[PDB]
Length: 256
Image (cartoon, rainbow, N blue to C red; front, side, top):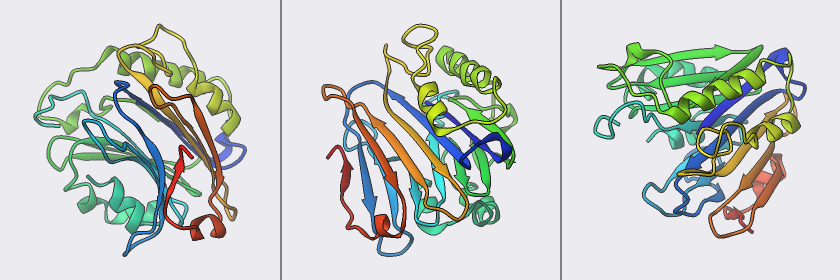
């Protein structure tokens, strides 16, 4: 998985959060809106079935968005919280506060949250150890390996794809000063470097979805999603998370 986003003069439509979900094409995913009994309503990029079902990404009505990356760097042995964020927190500051507990008890993982204000990257290591980064007027990017090795008990294992993919969105992003949603969409479909080391994989692992959202201040958030469930044809989502959107009943919005 490839995660990345821009904030500040680095974007022309506000905070951008993107996520490329890569995985063995052996399950089905779905975009679901949920109205939890206690918390904010939120959209979710669920993995209906498979080996690891659950929320892979989302965004709530308060306009807080988050995307996760698996921490393959370390053994499955040492390898949720994505839902707490979506249904109890409405801003990066809300998270920066309850972070030393929210993440101090979160399994290892890579998180990339975003809100009208900016972006925030969270790397949760072995046990409790976690590093934070908050950019407000620039760009951010992360894949499947820790940038701060200090958050682990021992040297990690960087996968060839996590390596290559990180160097690709890093390069492509460093070309222009500012970015847009339209651009990102093009970015997520880059087929540079074979079928395994590319942003849009198609080898052992296929990119099963493309997630991208824009969060302009004082305006409805705009979400675009490309679902690619194996066997089915590609389905694309384009929504405006306004008051009305969130008012609709909880149900699957992808695939129709």
